[PDB]
Amino acid sequence: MEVLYSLSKTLKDARDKIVEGTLYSNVSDLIQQFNQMIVTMNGNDFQTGGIGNLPIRNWTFDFGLLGTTLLNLDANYVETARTTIEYFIDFIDNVCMDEMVRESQRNGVAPQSEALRKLAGIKFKRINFNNSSEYIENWNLQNRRQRTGFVFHKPNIFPYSASFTLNRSQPMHDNLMGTMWLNAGSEIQVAGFDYSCALNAPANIQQFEHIVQLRRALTTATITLLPDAERFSFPRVINSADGATTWFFNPIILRPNNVEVEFLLNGQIINTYQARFGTIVARNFDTIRLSFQLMRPPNMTPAVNALFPQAQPFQHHATVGLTLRIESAVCESVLADANETLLANVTAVRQEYAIPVGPVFPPGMNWTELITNYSPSREDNLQRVFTVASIRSMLIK
Amino acid sequence: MEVLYSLSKTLKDARDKIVEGTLYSNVSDLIQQFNQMIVTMNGNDFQTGGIGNLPIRNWTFDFGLLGTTLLNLDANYVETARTTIEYFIDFIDNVCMDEMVRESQRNGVAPQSEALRKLAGIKFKRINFNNSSEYIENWNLQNRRQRTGFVFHKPNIFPYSASFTLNRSQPMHDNLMGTMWLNAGSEIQVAGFDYSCALNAPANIQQFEHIVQLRRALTTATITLLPDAERFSFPRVINSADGATTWFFNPIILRPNNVEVEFLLNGQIINTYQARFGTIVARNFDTIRLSFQLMRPPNMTPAVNALFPQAQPFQHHATVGLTLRIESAVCESVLADANETLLANVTAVRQEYAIPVGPVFPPGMNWTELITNYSPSREDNLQRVFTVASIRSMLIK
Amino acid sequence: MEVLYSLSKTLKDARDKIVEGTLYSNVSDLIQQFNQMIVTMNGNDFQTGGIGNLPIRNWTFDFGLLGTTLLNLDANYVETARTTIEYFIDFIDNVCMDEMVRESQRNGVAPQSEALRKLAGIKFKRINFNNSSEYIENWNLQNRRQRTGFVFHKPNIFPYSASFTLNRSQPMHDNLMGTMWLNAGSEIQVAGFDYSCALNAPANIQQFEHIVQLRRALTTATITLLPDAERFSFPRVINSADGATTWFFNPIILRPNNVEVEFLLNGQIINTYQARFGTIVARNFDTIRLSFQLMRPPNMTPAVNALFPQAQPFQHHATVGLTLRIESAVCESVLADANETLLANVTAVRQEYAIPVGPVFPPGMNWTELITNYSPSREDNLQRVFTVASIRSMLIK
Amino acid sequence: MEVLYSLSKTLKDARDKIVEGTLYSNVSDLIQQFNQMIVTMNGNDFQTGGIGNLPIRNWTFDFGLLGTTLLNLDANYVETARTTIEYFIDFIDNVCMDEMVRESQRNGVAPQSEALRKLAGIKFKRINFNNSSEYIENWNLQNRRQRTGFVFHKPNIFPYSASFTLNRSQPMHDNLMGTMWLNAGSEIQVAGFDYSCALNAPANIQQFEHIVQLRRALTTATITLLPDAERFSFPRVINSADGATTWFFNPIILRPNNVEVEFLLNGQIINTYQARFGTIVARNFDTIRLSFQLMRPPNMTPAVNALFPQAQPFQHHATVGLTLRIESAVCESVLADANETLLANVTAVRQEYAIPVGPVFPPGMNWTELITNYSPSREDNLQRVFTVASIRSMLIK
């Protein structure tokens, strides 16, 4: 796979640097690398594809070495180089597409795609050019056990889940208390609601707590934290716990008082933030514990007093919400992002050719289902296909 | 254009690599490139500016070469290189601004700005260093017809439009039905509202459809689809279609049921997702068809039963929402972004010097018009100007 | 594929110049070219077919060269020649069919068909003869991007569309204003109609508009504009707008007064012809904006007076008409035309061998839906297959 | 003119035959032609434009010659040739646009546009390559006065004219008899009509005759003649000849019995065809006499009898029609077609730059007024501008 990255990198650098009129000093080393690749690939045959609709293509390599007698590149040199490079780029695209569709429950990190296995053999090692990109760098760092890491803008760490838990309810659904939440991508919204606005509760303060259990621990995560969860602050009618009926929800947004956001690693408090909204930072964490409160306002003007009676009807339902966005972070494992398109490329490749559902990845590579159960073999296969997709996206956009 | 990018690249590399104390091994190739640039541009006169308020500046080049017998660079070397580099940097900045401010109805891709047009000659072909940047690489891959691509974060593809259609209405505006939608940049938010909560609809389901056609195909796009469109989930007062009288809106957010999202290319259905929210992928799509349904809930708690009567008033109006953010994508033609600053650079350079409204681009380069009408001439000019803006932004920030 | 065109050209020339009794000075150059072709192709085994019902074929070349020490050609020379040319024509025909059947969504300009993708290699650049034909020269220009153009006799730029709009209507469909149109191939036929003969219209003048939006802008188009669109100028019964009922239409034609035709190019009024008929010229345009008027006759013979009453019955329905035939045009991209058989050739090759549906083209190469949605990928695939079809038609008819 | 055509021809052949990898035997003669053109154009300062909105450009030539010993062309050779070819193509395009916009009452064939007049000298005679195209060959044959001929597909010889004559009439316009005709493009639709259905005519036969006089004699013209003119066979209301009143027209279509079409040159009856339809041939003619007859049905079923009464009112009016297309022809002078973009090119070139209205051509070059008055001087200027446009179409489309 290092060899595949090196082929992609030297093809990109050749299509970049080898231009009409550039000095030979600018591309002497690149020509050395290109000649190395050409000789090491010459007299060889590869077979790509044969899964799904992805067609069988046979590659045979026999090319001429780029010259060295030229003091300054001219149209002959450029044309010969590009006639070679088009062929090589199509080969690399096909190899990456072939590898992205294969899938192994056992030994995921090892290379599928017998063509790519032959590339991984012991006479193509001399094509290893440089492993500069983040994905290949982490690939090497993981193959020789070391501290990996990927910087993610807005990771999809959270499996999609919009739901609610009712700590107090009745079949009439007139007097409810609980927490609604939505975890999605990099966003958390929670809304603890009480229909009685903390009357029978002790001290007229109702406690609310929400736990979000990351499947992988993040690092140095810049996290925006704001009050007043938007999505749970307008009236709704929501199906019951089992769909039997539907209950009406009519929020009146109080302010969440003495909020406390804790970032936990294996149960140890790694960070805590007490009533400090706006940007904050989580050093290293795999669980988020948001503990907020609904305090009945002791002093109340006539309007809010009328909003909150003490009899049964409760025509307005008090609500306190929090919003929490992981703006950026650094994850040891590989995840989807908003900055990158690796998941898009992998799933598009799998959908182009109607690849049959393999063992480990869920159908259609549904990211929610993939991240809810993120077992080690699944993670290994995801890393392999993502790094291959990066190598492809180096050239095929 | 390629020569202009090469000049910018070598100047950036001269500003970076050529610093005091550096080994000559680290700067040998760049010094040879710099010497050739000096030699080829010596004894040549350029004249930039001369439109709007951009001052007419004459450039004449008479600069000495750089040494080779050193082992480690010192102050003398750096000082002479600095004096030359500042002059070339200013010259390149002014050439880029001159090329950005200009348009052309016919032959957009070909250069304007007689300085750059002179640069395009055979005499300067020896400057081409390496066309590494994404914009210049796509410039070459399109200048000779090949498959290009620009990767975008939150590509503001949709022109701004907030509007609504009413499939049932009457001047008292008491019993309406229809859709509202806001398309803005990268986000669609569509809300289908029925004032009767689908009382008399077949099977008590009201169907809503929203077709949005992009002006360019987006390849391998990652999208975030969620329910409960925020902006149409609170009470409003909205104009009539004719603007005569205003009508009240008072949403209760039902969920959308059997929601389908169809990503279509050239009419054919490329992808379709069936009640599956969260992160999704679209291989290709010239248009998006969001279809959903407002189903009257069969089992109604007394509260919601009170909300939805069979009488005429309908004091509360049922709604079902959808929101859809193109978190990232890849496009064959340039667009503005939330990550890049190319549009900002171009518009700022136009506004600084008060360039009169030209043939093709709208006044002020307002992206809404510029993407609403995206003729091939406008596309070609936008690509040229954006490539020049990237070339400038290499050196100037 | 310029090499493919060169093979086809040199085989056609060999068949059309190597004739018995002809001086060797007429075919010295072509014998040189043919020997170059033979030497280049010797030993190179090609493979063709393997899609749909197209048979798999293997092509092998070991051919001797033609004589050069002959003063004047004779029977034996021509017979050995034509033995070679028959085989070469067969190989070229198979390659062309294999390249027409195939199709590629991404990077559709590049060759499909492993035979042609091998011809694209470096060994075969010595076969390039010349690029004389319009299609091959436009192909070369676009590949090295320049302004190009195909000249078409009576293009079928318009997709078939016969329909109508009703500006005034009733459920009974007794008193209708509106427009009726048929766009088909090169002919627009638009007819406005008023059942009241502009009774209550302002000053007895009823305006009529018709926008038609060409998918690709045409250049230097010759147009024939006449009045009295014939197809909407006799009795009919037409389905309703939705399609429930039917309505009767009994046209008596008035003469269309102060007619105007505006040829626009992205909101750019390129040309305006007012009160002109017969041949006209639209130098460059993307939309045709037809306008005409129904003027009630100020004076009336009592026959006409009996036709047009003031009361409701309206037995006879006044109409105005316009026919607009695009005789010839120049289009930047390719289009089917009534002169050459490129589209017919491609569709014949597809149907003869039952090629399954591809990614980009519609089923059956249906021109109507191929031109309603004519995205760049579809356009370049169409250009590839059209150029290949021209290459084939040079030899096989 | 011969020189300018040779410039265009050799540039086209240089853009075609000089391609990468083509043998030198394929392009030797063309290379010598190119060298001759370069040598005899070097050091000449041409000037172009200065009328209307044409920019006043100045061209100066000092270009290098092309190699001679290389046995097979290569990329850099093509690159230098293309750098020269771009400039020369631009020069020719500008010169042809300059020449197409000039006129002269006296000596319209001699060159205007002083650049072309300079090219007409004795220095530039060595350029003359070969006069092969139709227009240049006719230009030579018609300068050194010989018989020439342009082949035209659908020649628009006829000026647009839609009108009628009334051999019987009244102040009502209630019992008429006469003819109507549309002569447009290459189409003659002539429809005789009689409101009495030839009731009282001698033997119930009404003889209709129509003489169409061409502005120039056509040769070997294929003509499609069909009965029942489709353009006048439906209801109408037609403003009177005076414009005072209107008159209703309600056709019922008889076929024309014993139709006879005579094609006349200089009075004599060159061709005559009686009761024949379909394709017919006029070897040489200048006028078309169409003579048909409306014969009352001797036997008549009750419905058609009810249509045709002996009384006055005549609710339905009998008509007999003819349609005559000139599918193809050969003409001595130049004309527009549906197969050539020469008129389109000239009119477009004048419109793009707003040439001042000249002495000889009509305003805007509308073909109807250009052909209706077609004096020899106007014909000569038309031939000159058309051949220049033909020269320009060899490079620019």
Image (cartoon, coloured by chain):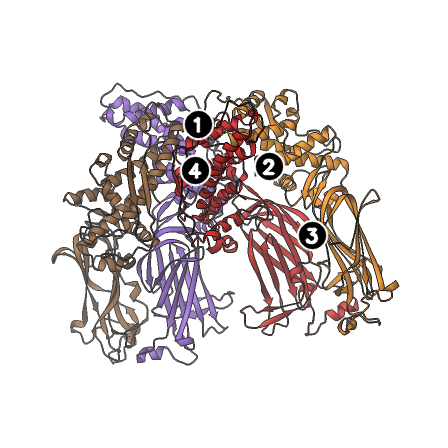
Chain colours: A brown, B purple, C red, D orange
Q: Residue furthest right?
A: D202
Mark 4 element type: loop
Give the label on residue D393, or none. Answer: 2
For label 1, the crowd category at 10 Å Cα-Cα, with few meaning under 14, some 14 to 19 and many 20 or more, is many
Q: Read off the residue under disc 1.
A: D74
Q: Kindly indicate whether the residues beneath marks 3 and 1 are on one polypeptide chain.
A: no
Amino acid bearing label 2:
Ser
Mark 1 element type: loop
Amino acid bearing label 1:
Asp
For label 2, the crowd category at 10 Å Cα-Cα, with few meaning under 14, some 14 to 19 and many 20 or more, is some
Between the C-alphas of marks 3 and 1, the distance is 57 Å
Between the C-alphas of marks 2 and 4, the distance is 25 Å
Q: Kindly indicate whether the residues beneath marks 3 and 2 are on one polypeptide chain.
A: no
Mark 3 element type: loop
Q: Read off the residue under disc 4.
A: B144
At which x and y percent is residue A168? 20, 75
Position of A361 with respect to C148 (left or right) is left
